[PDB]
Image (tube, rainbow, N blue to C red; front, side, top):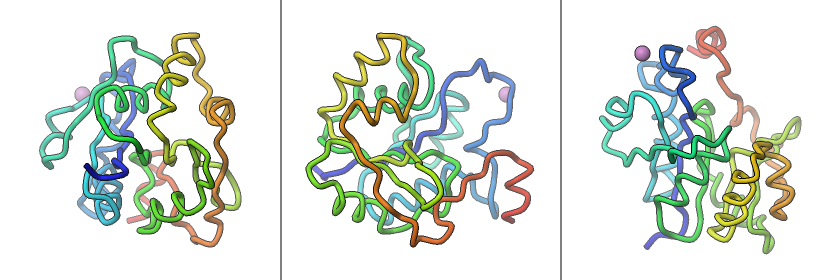
Length: 188
Ligand SMILES: [Li+]
């Protein structure tokens, strides 16, 4: 009943059981994934999180937690597809759990710039961020076919799907990501 569902991508898998859970690393007392979720909730009413470890911890802030299908597909696309299979509604705005400064015009600018394409993603002036992406429902069967073919490459898929980059180069540093606990330590 709203137009775009926001989605925090907190990562797959768990060949990572027993490793750092990056989305739960805290920045000024608040888990990174919640900084992303809170920024998406500024701009969208309905926001969910895709998480495959520590689900109970993710569930404690009261948002729906969506787990990957047993297919165990690789990479960020697998989370996107699991969310589309488990949520209704025609558009999704995905964002990884490690980019806590995303701006309040993310959804609005991606939508303004979509120009009829079924997918658009953020370019920050230096690089594409193809997991920060506004995706139409119609992508679901193409994603399923691509992952069932054993493919994983995110940019390749976005290109095959007819998407384009949207220029956010004027948003200084809104798209910086925390790659490691070492980097997080610097942003405190
Ligand atoms: Li653990």
